[PDB]
Length: 188
Length: 188
Image (cartoon, rainbow over all chains, first blue to last red; front, side, top):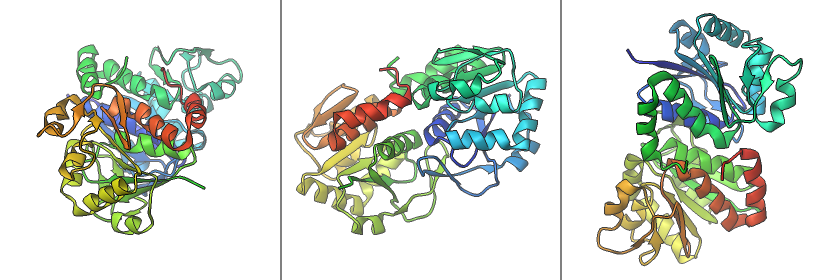
């Protein structure tokens, strides 16, 4: 009865956008797998924090399905996600089974690369808007967190707490999210 | 002419309180060393994120002095910091040379253990107040970020961005902090 989350971690990922959702989701009792795109080796993030994944994506792919698939941002991390055929397969499977897909900052640009969720309202970091909107396949939003169907998006490192708590609310409900929020000492 | 920061990373540290200041400080052009208390081995943080330090504390201790020494929180991480004689030596040296000391959440309780900054106004996580105030050696504050002389303290995971930007302002000034803040998409 435990919810499961897959976080895909690639070189160049934004380490704040990776660790905040992982931590907050584990505080909510969700079973989180941090899967390295290129294997189990440690991943050098965009500001040189090195994180050791829980598993390789190849291995984690076999232990699905997951209630949410989470794509962190970071410009170079998002580009690696966008070029990976394994990521394409996981996202299309998640879309087909109507599971949640969550992406932050530059992360949503990987949805466009893999043709996921066309027609949805989305947000991105302001610097990624033009990339995301190439072709007009989505409707753009400037909300700090946006949720349209099964696609949940957010804007930047500074929206990471709101992004993570929106995932918790979608999976475990509003009461659990409120209980997890209180000890964090968030402003609003 | 580059400022230098030492971040002391112990088992049980709060990984959000560790990565946010490291990332934000590197965005500000500060040279940051993440030093493992027990060595160079990877550190398992409080919510099971594993971070690989840049160096051991023993080695980093030799490459000082540092313009700021940063103590993350996490209950078990703070207890490890409080029991370490190497941490005592680094903090007393930093206090004697009038360098900045910064601690967040449960982190400030290590200052009490090592008798650092008695007489200063400090804040902590609400759950750590009674521990910090044992003996009445500090004056307690409920501000999200507090700075009294060379002691800079903050309350919780949710104050980590404000905490990190206060360090940047103290070291590099208000203009740099404002420039680093803008792309983060912070609310206030």
